Image (tube, coloured by chain):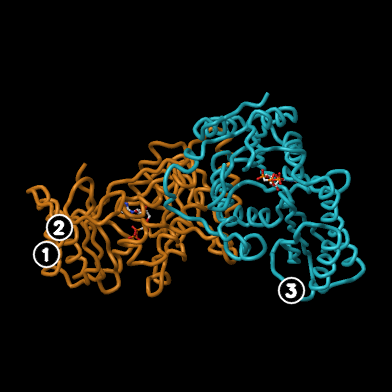
Chain colours: A orange, B cyan
C-alpha cells in the first residue's frame, strides 16, 4: 500500500488509471484513522478498482483556539490500517505542496455556512471546500466517500460538486459508532476516562429526541429543551449546540415538517464532539 | 463537420470516453461571434491534440447588471467557422444547465482583480473564473487556449489552475491582428471609416511604449504619459486607460524592473477597444 507524498506523482497515477479504465474511489481524511474511516474504505474497495485515502491535516479548516497543533498524527499506523482493508494509495502531500504561498482565488461557502457549525466555526467550511475541491482535481475519483456524522459538511460538499460540475459522485455513509453508541472520531482520544463515559449520552439524547418525535412531538423547542436538560444532568461538558434544522437545506425549524436533522455540539475539556440524527421524509 | 453538443451530460459522456481511449483534448472557451483570433487558437489545438472542443457560451456572470441579450449570437456561423479549421465539437450549454439555481459556493479573485478592468467592474473576473472552472471540470482538457488580448484574464486563469490543481495546461496565444496592426475583434466593424484609421494608433502607441523602453526608459509614469499623449493626438475616441503593471503579477512600481505589460482601453463612438503589449525580462 503506497504512500504518495507529492501532487505530481498522484496526478501521474490518476492519469494512468483513466487510460486503463481503472475506477477510483476516494476517502478524504485528516488521518488518525478509526473504524468510521475504515467503513468508508471498505465500501470503496468493494465498489472501485483502486481506492485512494488522503491523509492531510488541512490548516485552513482550523480556526483560532482549535486543535491544529494537537491534532493526532500517525501516518505509519494510518497506512497500516488502510492497507489491512485493501486500500491502494495513501495520498499525504506536504502543506507547502497543497498551499504554495497565498491563494490568488478564494472559495467561500454561502448560506449553508451561516448557521450551525458554520456560525460556531467561522471560515471552517471555506477551508473544507477549498481542500476538497483541490483533492478532487488531483485524484479525479469516480466516487468520493464522506461521513454523515458531519452532515452539514456533507450537504456543503454535495452543493460544491453541483456548483463546480465535478464529475465525482458523493456517497455519504451512516455514522459509525462504538458499541456504547459514541460516534467514532479521531478527537475521542482527547477525552478523559470519565468524559468518555459521559460522552455516550450525546448519542442517547438523540435516541431521546427520536422517541419524542416518534411519539408525536413536532415543537422543536420541546425537543431541544428535553435533549438539553437530559445532557445537562448527565455530562460535565459545555453544550454548545442543540438544534433542529431542515436537511439538507439547513433552515431552522420551529414546528417540524419534512426531513430534518437534530444536531449536537459539546465541548469537553479538550475534545469538541458532534453528533446528529436525520429524521423524516 | 463539428458536432454541436448542447448538454453538460453529453459533453461529460464524450470526455469520459476520450479519457479511456487515451484521446487528448484541447479546449478553446469563447462567447461566440468567432474571428481569426479565435481560429488561430483552434488551429493550434488541432495540430497538438486528438480532439478539439470549442465552447460558445455567453456567460451572464461576467457582464454588468444592465446588459441585454447586444452580444452577438450566431451559432451556425461559428460552428461552420471552427469546422473549417478541423474542430470536433462545439459545446453550447444552456445558461439554466450551467447555472440551475443560486450558487451555494462563491469563487472570488483576490489581488489580481484589484487593478485595471477588475477595479472598474468588481465581479467581472469572479464571473470569468466561475465559468472557466466549471468548463474545465466538464471538458477536462489537457490544454486550454486563451488569447493574450485579455492579459489580466490570462494571468487570473493561470492562477486559478494552480490554486485549484486543475490538470489542464494553459496556453496563451498571441494577439492576432489585421495587416495594419489593429487587434482583431467583433467591435471593429462598429468603427466609422475615419475611426477605423484612427484605431490603428492603439497598436502604434504600444510600439511607441516598447521603443521608449528599449531606449532605456524605466519610469512607468513617463511611458504612461508619453503613450497617453500620443494616443490623444491621433484619436477622436476617449482614453479609458493607459496602464503599466508587472506581468504576470499585476503590481505597479515607480521604477520598471522585470517583465511588464502596457495596456490600453479606448472608447470610440460605438466600439470599446483594448490592446496590450508584454515586454521586458
Ligand atoms: N463516526 C463516523 N462515522 C462515519 N463517518 C465518519 C465518522 N467520523 C468521521 N467520519 C468521516 O470521515 C471523514 C474524515 O473526517 P476527519 O475529520 O478526517 C476524522 P474525525 O475526527 O473522525 O471527524 P471530526 O474531526 O469531524 O470529529 C469525514 O467525511 C467524516 O464525516
Ligand atoms: N485578436 C485576438 N487574438 C488572440 N486572441 C483573441 C483575440 N480576440 C479574442 N481572443 C480570445 O478569444 C477568447 C474568447 O473571447 P470572447 O470571450 O469570445 C470575447 P472577445 O472575442 O475577446 O471579443 P472581441 O470580438 O472583441 O475579440 C479569449 O481568450 C480572447 O482573449
Instruction: Say whether marks 2 and 3 touch (CB < 8 Å).
Output: no
Tell me where residue A204 appears, x and y as whole percent. Answer: 15, 57
Identify the subunit bearing mark 2: A
Q: Nearer the viewer, residue A272 or B55?
A: B55
Query: CA gap, disc 2 to disc 3?
Result: 64 Å
Residue A31 vs A11, above or below: the answer is below
Q: Which residue is mark 1?
A: A230
Check disc 3 and report the residue beneath it. B253
Ligand 1 shown in quarter: bottom left
Q: Left of B249 or right of it: where is A246?
A: left
Left of B72 or right of it: where is B35? right
Q: Nearer the viewer, residue A181 or B153?
A: B153
Residue B125: horizontal and vertical position, in percent?
Answer: 59, 55
Q: In the displayed structure, does residue A125 sit left or right of residue A92?
A: left
Q: Earlier in the sequence, mark 2 or mark 1?
A: 2
> Which element type, helix, strand or loop, lies under badge 3?
loop
Residue that label 2 marks: A204
**A143 to the left or right of B61:** left
Q: Which mark is residue B125?
A: none
Image spot of residue A47 (x, y percent)? 40, 36
Amino acid at each position: 500500500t503506497k504512500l504518495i507524498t507529492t501532487v505530481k506523482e498522484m496526478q501521474h497515477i490518476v492519469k494512468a488509471a483513466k487510460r486503463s479504465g481503472t475506477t477510483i474511489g476516494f476517502i478524504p481524511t485528516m488521518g488518525a484513522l478509526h473504524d468510521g474511516h475504515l467503513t468508508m474504505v471498505r465500501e470503496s474497495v468493494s465498489t472501485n478498482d483502486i481506492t485512494v485515502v488522503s491523509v492531510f491535516v488541512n490548516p485552513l479548516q482550523f480556526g483560532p483556539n482549535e486543535d491544529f497543533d494537537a491534532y493526532p498524527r500517525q501516518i505509519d499506523k494510518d497506512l497500516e490500517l488502510v492497507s489491512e482493508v485493501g486500500a491502494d494509495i495513501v495520498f499525504h502531500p506536504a502543506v507547502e505542496d497543497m498551499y504554495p504561498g497565498e491563494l490568488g482565488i478564494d472559495v467561500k461557502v454561502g448560506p449553508l455556512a451561516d448557521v450551525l457549525e458554520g456560525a460556531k466555526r467561522p471560515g471552517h467550511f471555506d477551508g473544507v471546500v477549498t481542500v476538497v475541491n483541490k483533492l478532487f482535481n488531483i485524484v479525479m475519483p469516480d466516487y468520493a466517500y464522506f461521513g454523515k456524522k458531519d452532515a452539514q459538511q456533507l450537504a456543503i460538499v454535495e452543493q460544491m460538486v453541483k456548483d463546480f460540475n465535478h464529475a465525482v459522485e458523493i456517497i455519504g455513509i451512516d455514522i459509525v459508532r462504538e458499541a456504547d453508541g459514541l460516534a467514532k472520531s479521531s478527537r475521542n482520544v482527547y477525552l478523559t476516562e470519565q468524559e468518555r463515559q459521559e460522552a455516550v449520552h450525546l448519542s442517547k439524547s438523540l435516541l431521546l429526541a427520536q422517541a419524542l418525535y416518534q411519539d408525536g412531538e413536532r415543537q422543536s423547542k420541546v425537543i431541544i429543551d428535553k435533549v438539553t436538560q437530559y445532557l445537562e444532568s448527565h455530562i460535565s461538558g459545555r453544550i454548545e449546540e442543540v438544534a433542529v434544522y431542515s436537511y439538507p437545506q439547513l433552515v431552522e425549524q420551529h414546528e417540524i415538517t419534512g426531513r430534518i436533522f437534530i444536531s449536537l455540539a459539546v465541548k469537553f475539556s479538550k475534545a469538541r464532539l458532534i453528533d446528529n440524527i436525520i429524521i423524516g421524509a
